[PDB]
Length: 49
Length: 49
Image (tube, rainbow over all chains, first blue to last red; front, side, top):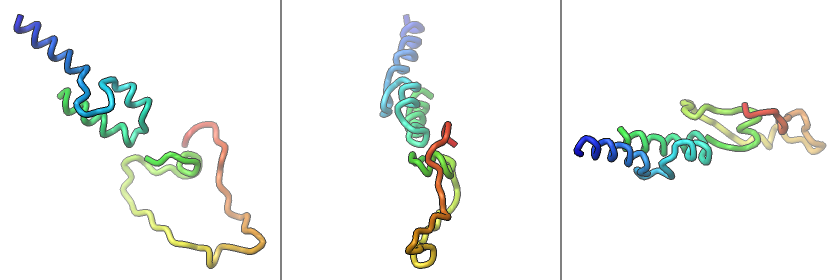
């Protein structure tokens, strides 16, 4: 159970925003220009790491 | 990170540009009553530069 739970959490936090516009990277890249998208991607990377 | 006609079709600075942009008015020298048509800018390109 513990193992499964950990994995589920590790996948569930892929859907978390971590202070960005959306959890989907492609949505952020499509909607925002590269200079503005850099900060959103940076927040997502910090959260996921 | 600026979007606009000049930025995308004439001269595009990089996202991580390191440099100084210096601008000063030239109306006293480069303006003619008849119309100085020497200076030109591009307004139709196939893709972004």
